């Protein structure tokens, strides 16, 4: 949404562009646009969503 | 000087003008071709037009 995807080698995070404050990639700070066959530079990773743990607690 | 891949920087700049960044990545080849041809036009304009 705002920021960039940064990896310290083995774990992917979202940070704001001007101050390194890392946060886990999640559905509330990244948006989605189609499938990923058109983008060059894609990397596979998990986008953990916050509703699934609450729903799985049921 | 902090370096960013030029594509991601162009995405930054599209966010700057109001267009979302996915528009660049989905259309990166087309945008590259437009920029290259636009630079090519300048050479004709300078060399030929007096
Ligand atoms: C990477 O850059 O950042 C990860 C941040 O999650 C780092 O992974 C965690 O590191 C802390 C501190 O060492 C550990 O307590 C955690 O167990 C570990 N894993 C998770 C899932 O939180 O992971 C990771 O170590 C780090 N890698 C490098 C090379 O710096
Ligand atoms: C990145 O920007 O540049 C890499 C250059 O190594 C790129 O990976 C591959 O590297 C081999 C090395 O011999 C080249 O022969 C390949 O052409 C090159 N692949 C491409 C697509 O150029 O790795 C890497 O792909 C490229 N990353 C992106 C997102 O373009
Ligand atoms: C990404 O994380 O996951 C994709 C899904 O499996 C991965 O795409 C696979 O690529 C291999 C090799 O090109 C193909 O043999 C598989 O058929 C293909 N899977 C699908 C569902 O299309 O695509 C993709 O490679 C992987 N990213 C990386 C960098 O490995």
Image (spheres, rainbow, N blue to C red):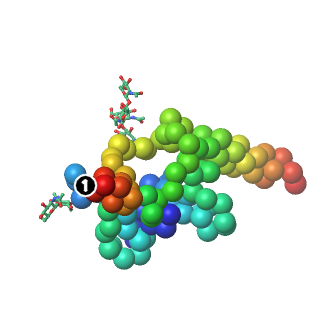
Secondary structure of residue under mark 1: loop
Residue A55 position, x and y percent, is: 35, 55
Could one spot residue A23 in this view of the protein? yes
For ligand 3, give the image quadrant.
top left
List the single residue furthest toward the bottom.
A19
Residue B8 position, x and y percent, is: 49, 56
Q: Is residue A6 above or below residue A44?
A: below
Relative to B3, B15 lies left or right: right
Q: Which is nearer the eye, B26 or A27?
A: A27
Could one spot residue A5 in this view of the protein? no
Residue B27 position, x and y percent, is: 62, 44
Q: Which is nearer the eye, A55 or B9?
A: A55
- The residue depicted at 43 percent of the width and 70 percent of the height is A17
List the single residue furthest toward the right.
B50
- The residue depicted at 72 percent of the width and 48 percent of the height is B38
- Residue receiving disc 1: A11
Chain letter behind tag 1: A
Q: Quadrant of the C terminus of chain A?
A: bottom left
- The residue depicted at 24 percent of the width and 58 percent of the height is A8
Q: Which is nearer the eye, A15 or A49?
A: A49
- The residue depicted at 52 percent of the width and 51 percent of the height is A32
Residue A54 position, x and y percent, is: 33, 60
Beta carbon of the mark 1 residue lies under 8 A of ligand 1 = yes
Q: Residues within 10 Å of mark 1 (few under 14, many from 20)?
A: few
Q: Which is nearer the eye, A50 or A14?
A: A50
**Residue B20 in which image quadrant:** bottom right
């Amino acid at each position: 949404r705002e920021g960039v995807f940064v990896s310290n080698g083995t774990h992917w995070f979202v940070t704001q562009r001007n101050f390194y404050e890392p946060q886990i990639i999640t559905t509330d700070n990244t948006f989605v646009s189609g499938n990923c066959d058109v983008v060059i530079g894609i990397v596979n990773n998990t986008v953990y969503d916050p509703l699934q743990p609450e729903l799985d607690s049921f | 000087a902090l370096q960013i891949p030029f594509a991601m920087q162009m995405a930054y700049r599209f966010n700057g003008i109001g267009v979302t960044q996915n528009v660049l990545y989905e259309n990166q080849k087309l945008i590259a071709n437009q920029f290259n041809s636009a630079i090519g036009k300048i050479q004709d304009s300078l060399s030929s037009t007096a």
